Amino acid sequence: MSHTILLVQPTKRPEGRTYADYESVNECMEGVCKMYEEHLKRMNPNSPSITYDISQLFDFIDDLADLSCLVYRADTQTYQPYNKDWIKEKIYVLLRRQAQQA
Image (cartoon, rainbow, N blue to C red; front, side):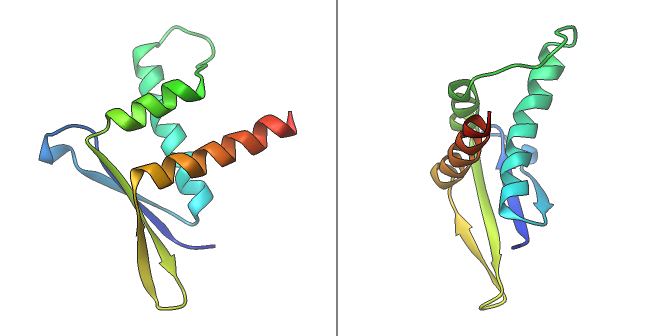
């Protein structure tokens, strides 16, 4: 698995820049969905389930001022960068697999 770092900046405000790290690319993508999920729970404290469609996720990601990831390559002991659109496609594929399973 490749160690992965996610850099997020929610708004134009520089002090909001944050990061988190994961043991793999798929756990980082799941981390992106968890970010949106905890945002929806803040907003909806009294909804029993947090439910959302993939279009709502994608608009949330598009609205971030910035989102990128760095993925460790054993090859060169270095990190390959990938942009917001790459991220969205991995989450697409991930969420599409689960939907098939069901």
